[PDB]
Amino acid sequence: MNIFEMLRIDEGLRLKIYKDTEGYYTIGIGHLLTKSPDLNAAKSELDKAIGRNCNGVITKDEAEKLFNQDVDAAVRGILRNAKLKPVYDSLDAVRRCAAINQVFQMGETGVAGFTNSLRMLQQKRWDEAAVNLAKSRWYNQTPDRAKRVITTFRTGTWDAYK
Ligand SMILES: Cc1ccc(Cl)cc1O
Image: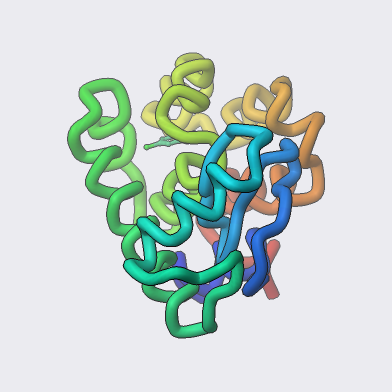
């Protein structure tokens, strides 16, 4: 297991524009195109991201290319964030994957609501952190995925991903 395999499980792979769990146009392995309800705006974002006229469809290679860009940018964002970097750098590599996963899903603005969880994770109070993480819109809206990510934070193992 690694961050790519982990996010591939959690996000799936779809080659045509679809709506994510929040109703937002998306493609590939959880590549958000836009929060706009306008499908045309989404198609324009897709063409911009791929560099050709896609008419709402991409190939697996193209999906994986966006995925690599998206995972990388997520990590680099964490490292630039004064609130996130110290927590991230305190963690072992398996737990760092859980961190990347959560940021990939909800963005840094999403993880801003997790200040108390962050503190417990930095303190390595793993069961306490796991309890606090589940007290969230995140958990309630995507409980099966959040359970997997939280187990990863709690144990530092890949048990939740088989
Ligand atoms: C919970 C959590 C901790 C540390 C980082 Cl870097 C991200 C997270 O989404």
